[PDB]
Amino acid sequence: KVPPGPNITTNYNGKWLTARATWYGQPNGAGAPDNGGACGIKNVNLPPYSGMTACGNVPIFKDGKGCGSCYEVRCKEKPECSGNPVTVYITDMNYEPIAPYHFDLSGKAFGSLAKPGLNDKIRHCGIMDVEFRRVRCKYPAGQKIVFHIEKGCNPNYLAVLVKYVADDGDIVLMEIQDKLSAEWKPMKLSWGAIWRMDTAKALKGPFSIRLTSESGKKVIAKDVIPANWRPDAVYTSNVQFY
Ligand SMILES: *[C@@H]1O[C@H](CO)[C@@H](O[C@@H]2O[C@H](CO)[C@@H](O[C@H]3O[C@H](CO[C@H]4O[C@H](CO)[C@@H](O)[C@H](O)[C@@H]4O)[C@@H](O)[C@H](O[C@H]4O[C@H](CO)[C@@H](O)[C@H](O)[C@@H]4O)[C@@H]3O[C@H]3OC[C@@H](O)[C@H](O)[C@H]3O)[C@H](O)[C@H]2NC(C)=O)[C@H](O[C@H]2O[C@@H](C)[C@@H](O)[C@@H](O)[C@@H]2O)[C@H]1NC(C)=O
Image 1 (cartoon, rainbow, N blue to C red):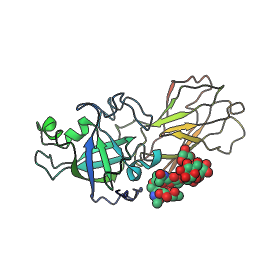
Image 2 (cartoon, rainbow, N blue to C red; image 1 turned 30 degrees about the horizontal axis):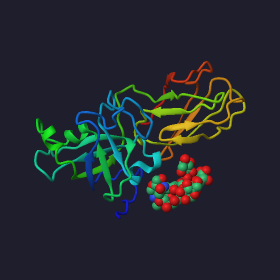
Image 3 (cartoon, protein in one colour; image 1 turned 60 degrees about the vertical axis):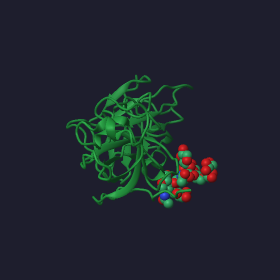
Image 4 (spheres, protein in one colour; image 1 turned 180 degrees about the horizontal axis):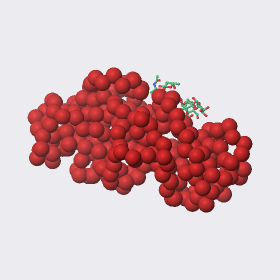
């Protein structure tokens, strides 16, 4: 049995750590056959993620609190290795105790670690020792944080997904407050980047949401939730982590 890392914090100490990488799914896909993952963010194949997805064990993944993080991995062991790093997003998980730190890259990502034209070649080594370090996350400019409403059930129990969180990348607490009776009530971490609000009878009127990065940093989106909100509906805010 192989014991996990630790466990990576928001301590951005720009230096490389060892880890074993492998890939899963299609060779030119974004990992999950459905292009989604343990985090609950979907379309990880399309931009911005654009298939540069990956999986990590407890240390990296952190039971869903690492969802959003960005890491930089590079290969310099076996040939055909670009030598240069690729910026990966953590949108899924894999807890197999095969090594202290483990990354399970997409075919796209795993390939990107290779010198131009050697992709598919390098993808057939399956497992190799890579090097990495977490990094703040950068998205296209102007790209703010987006909240997606999930498929409901019992009369309004909500559940919001949060994507495109720059810098820390990952969330560790969400909370609300409707029009009147402010005080920011927490939220349940249903799973991954999905947060749940059991009660919803009282909570009425454009809601404000406060996110707290792994670091403690916080932000506030006033509306982003009218009232005529319907599951699947998507809201974009004017707030982000710098
Ligand atoms: C490396 O990162 C990992 C990834 O998170 C860290 O390890 C996780 O740390 C969590 C600490 O919050 C642990 O807590 C969960 O498990 C607790 C133990 O529960 C016993 O009974 C429950 C029954 O429900 C079983 O499931 C468990 O298996 C266990 O046998 C559990 O009590 C706790 O929930 C309770 O406390 C929280 C506040 O801590 C509270 O909000 C809850 O309402 C409840 O009162 C918690 O359960 C969670 O899982 C499901 C989520 O939906 C819930 O919201 C959440 O409560 C995790 O077990 C643990 N994960 C692993 C290692 O598999 C780790 O921080 C470490 O954390 C410390 C506290 C200790 O658990 C270490 O062993 C653990 O490695 C980090 N490394 C380190 C060392 O920092």
